[PDB]
Length: 118
Ligand SMILES: *C(=O)CCCCCCCCCCCCC
Image (cartoon, rainbow, N blue to C red; front, side):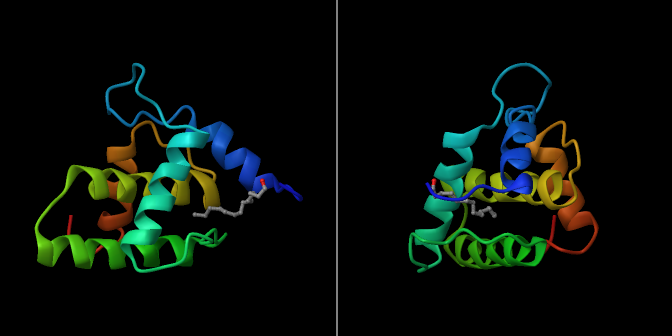
């Protein structure tokens, strides 16, 4: 609540277009949503609530971590969603990509060899 950033406001505004439901009709991301993901995923990774990086490396790292934990534990829609959120935001943010659906973004991150397994 002090300083602002280009990639920050640009990422959020763009994320609004991202289709979390995957289909191209409502159910898109946003400010509150993006926060709910990073916030939850943060605590899940035994990391303080003040986790707000600004590098594609930091994002891809958080994913691999949360994935590893959620993996050995099984699978959870909640945590799963948070992951896909940080993914689309990372690509559509750092890469300023126009992710049509959170699902597509995650597919690219993994397809490129960033996210462990599909
Ligand atoms: C005042 O409102 C403080 C909150 C503003 C934080 C700025 C954004 C910091 C960078 C986070 C980017 C997300 C990376 C996954």
